[PDB]
Image (tube, rainbow, N blue to C red; front, side, top):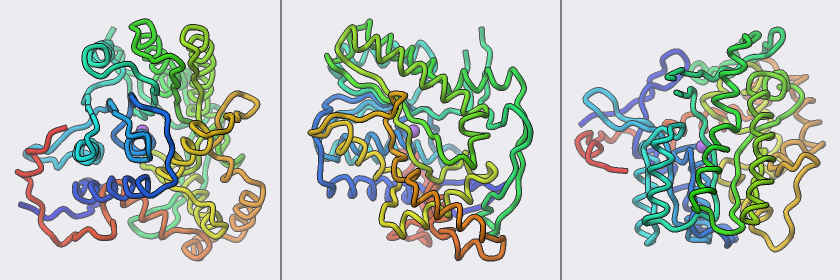
Length: 397
Ligand code: NA
């Protein structure tokens, strides 16, 4: 029986507020329940289903109109003697509670998605109990990958020279300059192993050859391109190299699925959102804060769930044909990269100071979204209320 507070250690919040996480899940569900609605997917596999885009994907297909049954694969840990548990751990639990209330299947595999054991387990469940899958979304954003037993670690670096610029320190409400430098050859390769398209492709092949995909099944992975201002990181750097690998694999998966089941694969390039991993990378967080202000002013702002909802209802499962860019990618950053939006961001950038940034950018919204990632600062949650830790320990995914 304890009060959970937001304690910052080396820039990151230590604990998560589980009921704040519940509320965030519920806010996304609410958005989807009230949106125009779409139809299509019935049986959906999501690898990386516990947070961010994977979670929004799951909520969207379940509550956004299709009433899809879902399998979520994620590695998360619960409450112990000393730890409260990860946000994703709770997101899984609360998603399942709300999905079942609607009479939907919401299976969780709390498992390392990279291992052959996990694939076998998921495949067995599909063949035995779930039924064939019409949509497979790969949205794992793991920091490392275990293979023999080599461990590969993702890094966020340039391939040449320094990248430096402002980050947002949420704890002190200030801008702070940071720098990241060049990656080693091994670091580039490891990042490609973790973030590239290899595991996604393995999944698609196992699923395909084990007769787990429905005819005409779709599979999707997520990426980010952004503005030229951060190309050194997101296109040219270690992340950019991994994402090009992801894009290349999408093409090979697409060709195969098309030939074998009339299915398809593609990368959806999404918009800038606040995440833990991009906090403290130089120059992105300020970009995002300014972007939020501009797009909110222009009535075109989207958070994670809004991105996904529009992706599904307006582009993927719409009446009209799907439009890809010239490299076969679905572009959900079409509003972010709109000329008028980028012109305004660059203008504000040229006036922004460490002194005035809270007025020229959406620092408030940036900070709120950051806090929300650990279940803090959610409207309608009583943070003075103590939490029953033995009750939380009882919850099962
Ligand atoms: Na995800």
